[PDB]
Amino acid sequence: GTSKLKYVLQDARFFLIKSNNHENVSLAKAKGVWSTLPVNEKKLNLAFRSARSVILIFSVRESGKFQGFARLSSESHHGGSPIHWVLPSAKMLGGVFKIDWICRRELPFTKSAHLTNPWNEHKPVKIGRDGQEIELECGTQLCLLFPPDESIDLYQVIHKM
Image (cartoon, rainbow, N blue to C red):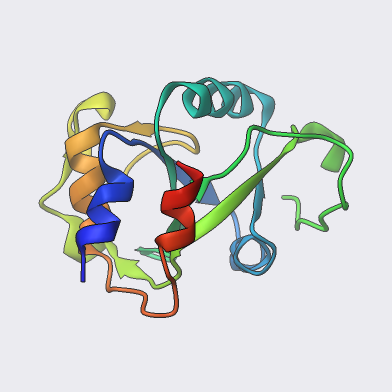
């Protein structure tokens, strides 16, 4: 069902993550981690303190799709296991966020054409820079459009809230 998902998304904040390649999203899906440039790191750390859930919605550039979404489980930290990102240069990144995936399935942009983001001039939600915040209602409806991921159990994520 969709009820535990709606509970996790209640009063959440949402951010668009744009990856240059599929390899980095595959690493994030396998290891449960993301890293971003310091300007976005600071925004995500502020958001993590401010909201019950902070949701990252991932899209690989030129793919025409979103590849899934995940919830921050920590602020960023330094000095863990090093991550061999494909950088498009590793010293330029900030710390590492731990994330819990909520959906690892794809959603094509053609299915989100009716959703506009007020925080980006009401452009279609697919449009945005890496780190663009997505307003609550747009972000909630976007996450509810993804196919259900029946491999994930949100019981443990609810306990982290």
